[PDB]
Amino acid sequence: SKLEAILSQEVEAEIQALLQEAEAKAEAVKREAEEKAKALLQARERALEAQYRAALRRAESA
Amino acid sequence: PVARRKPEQFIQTGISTIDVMNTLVRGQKLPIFSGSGLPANEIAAQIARQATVRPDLSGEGEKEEPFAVVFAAMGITQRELSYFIQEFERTGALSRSVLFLNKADDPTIERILTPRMAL
């Protein structure tokens, strides 16, 4: 019957909202990582080069 | 008396705190109160080598400033004496410096004059 149909009618749109929330919750996890990984590695590239050149320079000073 | 002029120019040190709280400038006599068994000594030749005479930031260059590092110890122990050889000698950091240093072992008489030299 139709009564319980309204109970149906309520659930289906909620199934979709769990998903929409979820979708955003996977993506964000993904995106938090994207910037973070990229941003440290830059710094560690940077740092390693300087920690080299200045030595070689100081070596040139020898 | 008519030669001297009141300070007007910072100089960087390679140390932070000792430029922030108390800020290095040229023609400044900064006493550095040490105590007994301490690595004062270290932080000397340490921040020594770090040093580079600088006022770039003010709007000047740094090309026409010769950097003269003059180093003088006294009363040096076997141990310490090599730390010296370690810093200058590390690379060519004697590339801008001279040592002078009357050991305890050495006469205390010659000692006296020691500074007066580099002075």
Image (cartoon, coloured by chain):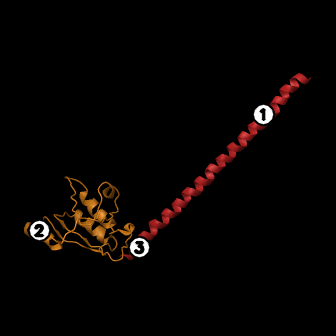
Q: Which one is nearer the viewer's eye here, B54 or A28?
A: B54
Q: Amino acid at mark 2?
A: Arg
Q: Which mark is residue B111?
A: 2
Percent coordinates x, y for residue B92 in the rendering: 33, 74
Dot 2 and dot 3 within a common chain: no
Q: Chain of mark 3?
A: A
Q: Which mark is residue A14?
A: 1
Q: At 80% across and 34% down in the image, what residue appears?
A: A13
Q: CA distance from mark 2 to mark 3?
A: 36 Å
Tell me the red chain: A
Point out the image quarter for the N terminus of chain A. top right
Q: Which residue is mark 3?
A: A57
Q: Residue furthest front?
A: B2
Q: CA distance from mark 1 to mark 3?
A: 65 Å
Q: Secondary structure at mark 1?
A: helix
Q: Secondary structure at mark 3?
A: helix
Q: Are the residues at dot 2 and dot 3 in contact (C-beta closer than 8 Å)? A: no
